[PDB]
Image (cartoon, coloured by chain):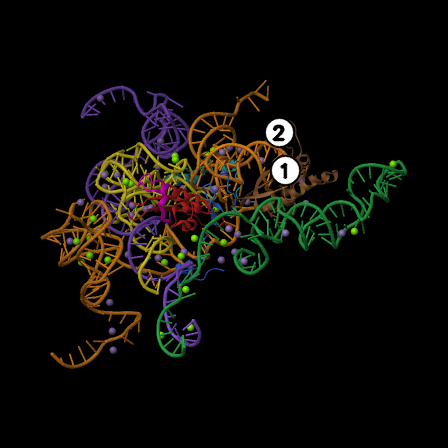
Chain colours: A red, B brown, C blue, D cyan, E purple, F yellow, G orange, H green
RNA sequence: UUAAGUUAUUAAGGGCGCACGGUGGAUGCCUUGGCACUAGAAGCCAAUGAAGGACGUUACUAACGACGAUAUGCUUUGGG
RNA sequence: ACCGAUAGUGAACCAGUACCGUGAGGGAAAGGUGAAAAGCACCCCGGAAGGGGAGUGAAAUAGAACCUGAAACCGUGUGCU
RNA sequence: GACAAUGGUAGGAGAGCGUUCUAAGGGCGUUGAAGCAUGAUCGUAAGGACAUGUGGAGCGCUUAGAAGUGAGAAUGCCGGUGUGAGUAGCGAAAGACGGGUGAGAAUCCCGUCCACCGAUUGACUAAGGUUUCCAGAGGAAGGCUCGUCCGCUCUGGGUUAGU
RNA sequence: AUGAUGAGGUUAAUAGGUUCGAGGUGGAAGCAUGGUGACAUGUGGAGCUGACGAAUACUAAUCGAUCGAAGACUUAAU
């Protein structure tokens, strides 16, 4: 129907990816790519590549007209997180969380 | 009067940035350094536009040594190019032989990049 | 000094309403295609 | 600062060696015990 | 329109309900391993070099076993 | 009328081993795809990772970090506010 | 059918709910068991059913028997995940531009200029450490950022003595 | 601090430059002369000069996008 694509365990924290994701959500696919290319945060290129792949198999698979396509929905979910430490003063170690996330984008036409 | 580093290191980077771009007409830098360097460069170009040994020995006080490779054979000096090359171009021109072009943010630190070029 | 009571999901989100990023000011390249940031260079074309 | 433990190959092998264990009844008792637990290292 | 009075829409964001997801590894089912006994065998190995190891052996070999320089096996009797 | 993976041995996994101590010594965690590897040919976006089709299968909303997949916790949509 | 009584801590007395296993009887189950989820269901309570989804092989009921039989608190033990919060920190120090490379460079290579140590940040070697040394590839994780790079990864090599 | 306030955005003096100037310093370099020289005088209130003051579009404020009214009901009064 109205196509989607997903990237899994990207190693950016979900809070961080979500910031870029909010600007893109609900927007026309073209300007979505624009806002993505100009927004200078770290997650922007990653999210870009995901939206590109989404529109790509929205055409090669479901044969929609790419230009009428809209970013119907985008989000990021907590992935598994790598756990590391960080030695400190007095010889105590302390926690560090290298978190990762599943980014999802879904583009669209009309209802049918 | 913008800074970045310490008062002397700032001097050094400014002479370095100024000598460069005389060496090669245009360079890429932070917007802040571009706005600082433009003054030092137009000023060196007026010392060049005067022509006297006074203002030459004067341009020498700031400008770096360098080497410069002229097209085909032979070697100039950044000084020699300031007085014996660039100044020839800008005699009829009034003030302001410089422009900053706004490249936008770079990856590593997101500093805003700009090109700074001659005419 | 330490927090004396944990923040609730509600308090923490209310504290975050202003923590967005603004959509960049942007403009179409005249007859070049890719859009660029405002009052910034048009690139190599 | 000068931490405890400056390594020394000779001194480590004297005092803590197979042979040094063997040299007294108790060292043999030690090797006995470690053999009983089945340490992959035993005395070293 | 003028005066007096009365109401509402807005949600930056929040709350309740619901839907769809993610994380996480409880719960159910499973058992290669354990746990306590029963009946019978057996209760010693060692200078003819032990117990326990070290280093090696395979087309390719890091690890475990097996084997030792006749090395990932040799002869021999029987089973298959 | 014993345990069923926080149990039962410390050890159901190449355990007295990662790891820790100069040493004597201390001492873990870690089981499960499927009936069968049939473990996704090929096309597509991507440097790759990862993914959408197309397929194997009763099932992959069983795809390997793989049975079931609770709660905390994180999100997207919105009916009343 | 009238009548009486029924607040309650320590504590005594009574009657019951549910969990695992066992025995006997009687049943359910791939036309879908347990489990999980949802619901406007039922009983005086603990608690019991029914329908739908999920799940993919086991499980109730009756009578009795036996217990590792019921958790919210022990600065309890293990595991997961929050809050603090996009907060503290990123470990003494001078760097700039040009040119390469690359999917991608403040951070890798080359270049010029600048700078810092110079009884030492230089050159040897003992202790200790044991392939970190060299070459070509690589970039998941390690590196407090980045990475095309590395004391990291893969593949292949490298230590020669009568004195 | 950031935002905020204010001065401007080509029909333009908002910054930078350029040419002038205030103020600061105190007599640049090069040459000439006088000395054996270290130095002195002349050329010449010289030269240089961040923030301060004018003038001047030479450089840069380009193109462009976003947001923002159509005016509720009742009663009395023209
Ligand atoms: Mg032991
Ligand atoms: Mg009124
Ligand atoms: Mg209004
Ligand atoms: Mg909103
Ligand atoms: Mg006997
Ligand atoms: Mg019993
Ligand atoms: Mg000790
Ligand atoms: Mg491609
Ligand atoms: Mg490709
Ligand atoms: Mg399919
Ligand atoms: Mg599939
Ligand atoms: Mg029951
Ligand atoms: Mg039933
Ligand atoms: Mg079903
Ligand atoms: Mg229920
Ligand atoms: Mg009973
Ligand atoms: Mg507790
Ligand atoms: Mg902040
Ligand atoms: Mg190594
Ligand atoms: Mg290596
Ligand atoms: Mg003389
Ligand atoms: Mg004067
Ligand atoms: Mg508009
Ligand atoms: Mg009214
Ligand atoms: Mn320490
Ligand atoms: Mn100094
Ligand atoms: Mn990067
Ligand atoms: Mn929010
Ligand atoms: Mn031991
Ligand atoms: Mn017996
Ligand atoms: Mn004998
Ligand atoms: Mn033996
Ligand atoms: Mn035979
Ligand atoms: Mn165990
Ligand atoms: Mn389990
Ligand atoms: Mn199997
Ligand atoms: Mn693939
Ligand atoms: Mn099929
Ligand atoms: Mn898992
Ligand atoms: Mn599963
Ligand atoms: Mn009572
Ligand atoms: Mn009463
Ligand atoms: Mn009692
Ligand atoms: Mn069926
Ligand atoms: Mn059961
Ligand atoms: Mn039944
Ligand atoms: Mn109990
Ligand atoms: Mn608890
Ligand atoms: Mn805990
Ligand atoms: Mn704070
Ligand atoms: Mn702070
Ligand atoms: Mn900070
Ligand atoms: Mn550092
Ligand atoms: Mn290139
Ligand atoms: Mn270099
Ligand atoms: Mn020095
Ligand atoms: Mn050594
Ligand atoms: Mn070491
Ligand atoms: Mn090396
Ligand atoms: Mn890194
Ligand atoms: Mn304003
Ligand atoms: Mn004018
Ligand atoms: Mn003056
Ligand atoms: Mn405009």
- Provide the secondary structure element on which disc 2 rests: loop
Of the residues under marks 1 and 2, which one precedes in the sequence?
1
Q: Residue G42: image x %, image y %?
A: 18, 64
Q: Total marks drawn? A: 2
Instruction: Tell whether H73 sits left or right of D1.
Output: left
Q: Position of residue D24 (x, y in %)?
A: 45, 38
Pinpoint residue D29: horizontal percent, then vertical percent.
41, 40
User: Eyeballing the image, is H77 above or below D18?
Assistant: below
In magenta, the rendered stretch is A53-78
Relative side of G38 to A86, left or right? left
A8 is within the stretch colored magenta: no
Dot 1 crowding, Cα within 10 Å, few <14, some 14–19, many 20+? many
Residue under pointer 1: B22
Q: Mark number for residue B71?
A: 2
Q: Quadrant of residue A8?
A: top left
Q: Is residue A73 magenta?
A: yes
- Nearer to us in this view, G59 or C24: C24
Q: Could you tell me if residue A82 is visible in this image?
A: no
Name the quadrant containing residue D39.
Answer: top left
Residue D9, above or below A77: above
Discs 1 and 2 lie in a common subunit: yes
Whether residue A42 appears in this view of the structure is yes
Q: Residue at x 41, y 58 (%)?
A: C13
Q: Residue sitting at 64 percent across and 32 percent down? A: B68
Quadrant position of ligand 61: bottom right
């Amino acid at each position: 129907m109205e196509a989607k694509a997903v990237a899994r365990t990207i190693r950016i924290a979900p809070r961080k990816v979500r910031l870029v994701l909010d600007l893109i959500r609900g927007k026309n696919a073209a300007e979505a790519i624009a806002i993505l290319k100009l927004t200078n945060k770290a997650s922007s290129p990653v999210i870009e590549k995901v939206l590109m792949s989404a529109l790509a198999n929205a055409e090669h698979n479901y044969d929609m007209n790419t230009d009428e396509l809209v970013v119907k929905e985008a989000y990021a979910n907590e992935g598994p997180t790598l756990k590391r430490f960080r030695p400190r003063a007095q010889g105590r170690a302390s926690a560090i969380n290298k978190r990762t996330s599943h980014i999802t984008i879904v583009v669209s036409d009309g209802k049918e | 009067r913008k800074l970045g580093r310490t008062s002397d290191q700032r001097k050094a980077m400014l002479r370095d940035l100024a000598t460069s771009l005389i060496i090669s007409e245009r360079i890429e830098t932070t917007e802040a350094r571009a706005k600082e360097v433009r003054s030092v460069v137009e000023k060196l170009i007026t010392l060049g536009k005067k022509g006297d040994l006074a203002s030459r020995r004067n341009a020498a006080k700031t400008l770096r040594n360098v080497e410069i490779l002229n097209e085909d054979e032979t070697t100039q000096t950044a000084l020699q190019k300031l007085f014996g090359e660039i100044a020839e171009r800008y005699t009829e021109r009034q003030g302001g032989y410089t422009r900053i072009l706004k490249q936008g943010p770079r990856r590593g630190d997101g500093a805003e990049s700009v090109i700074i070029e001659l005419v | 000094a330490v927090p004396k009571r944990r923040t609730s999901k509600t308090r923490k989100n209310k504290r975050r309403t202003h923590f967005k990023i603004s959509v960049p000011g942007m403009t179409e390249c005249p007859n070049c295609g890719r859009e660029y940031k405002l009052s910034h260079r048009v690139c190599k074309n | 600062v000068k931490r405890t433990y400056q390594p020394n190959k000779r001194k480590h092998s004297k005092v803590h060696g197979f042979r040094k264990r063997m040299s007294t009844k108790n060292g043999r008792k030690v090797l006995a015990r470690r053999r009983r637990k089945g340490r992959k290292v035993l005395s070293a």
